[PDB]
Image (cartoon, rainbow, N blue to C red):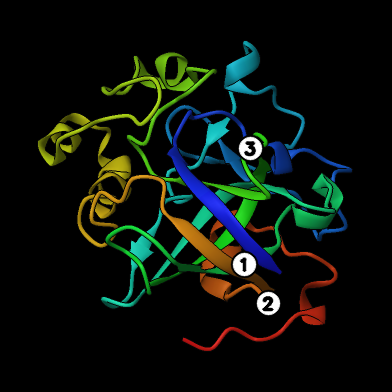
Amino acid sequence: SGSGQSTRYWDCCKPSCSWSGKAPVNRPVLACDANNNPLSDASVKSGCDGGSAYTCANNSPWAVNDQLSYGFAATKLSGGTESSWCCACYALTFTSGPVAGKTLVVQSTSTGGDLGSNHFDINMPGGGVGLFDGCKRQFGGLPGAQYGGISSRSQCDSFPAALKPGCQWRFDWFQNADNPNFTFKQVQCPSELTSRTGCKRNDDSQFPVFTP
């Protein structure tokens, strides 16, 4: 459905698609308590608003081969609304930086800030908390700059264990790419992603199957 710019983030906040009535889905994205246990109760208040609900650690990216990874993102799309992108999946093909040519299929779990025509803020632990430091409340905070997060792969060594794979993915398969550009198209969600969030759009079948 177009081209866009990526950034990186992990702020630990309850994802905005974890709330009820936001999109036509079977159920909202599962958030987690501070100890990474899934919350079936979608009314729990976000740890970024004085509450106790956080992003589940399984909202992390991973590689299945040197060409293809799966992950999650906050999206802000031209012509769209939360009701059209929450729990939708998109295949991104990177067009710049060291990852140019690689493919990342993400599910949207949240609404991102406006940046360019179709911003994808890609989840990766240690990518930066930005404006809301929920990770401070969840477990005392993550190292790293407010925007961009950590700068060395060793800094992943002190993360909560469940956050270390996604932290290291950023330096391994993602090659520490700094805000690469991409083209993207909406696709049916691989079960790899909807099994983690539990959230599947009623219109999922309206879009093409992803072929690796």
Query: Which amino acid type is shown beneath numbered disc 1?
Result: Tyr
Identify the disc placed on residue 15: 3
- Residue occupying the far left of the picture: 154
Q: CA distance from mark 2 to mark 3?
A: 21 Å
Q: Are marks 2 and 3 in contact (CB under 8 Å)?
A: no
Answer left or right for 82 relative to 97: right
Q: Secondary structure at mark 2?
A: loop
Q: Eyeballing the image, is 36 above or below 143?
A: below
Q: CA distance from mark 1 to mark 2?
A: 8 Å
Q: Nearer the viewer, mark 1 or mark 2?
A: 1
Name the residue carrying label 1.
90
Q: Earlier in the sequence, mark 3 or mark 1?
A: 3
Nearer-the-camera pick, 45 or 189: 189
Q: Eyeballing the image, is 42 above or below 27?
A: above
Query: Which amino acid type is shown beneath numbered disc 2?
Result: Gln
Answer left or right for 58 relative to 39: left
Asked whether residue 195 is in view, the answer is no
Query: Which amino acid type is shown beneath numbered disc 3?
Result: Pro
Q: Earlier in the sequence, mark 1 or mark 2?
A: 1
What residue is drawn where x is 63% and y is 72%? Answer: 189
Query: Which x, y percent locates residue 5?
Result: 53, 50
Identify the disc placed on residue 188: 2
Q: Secondary structure at mark 1?
A: strand
What residue is drawn where x is 70% and y is 37%? Answer: 16
Which quadrant would residue 115 be assigned to in this image? top right
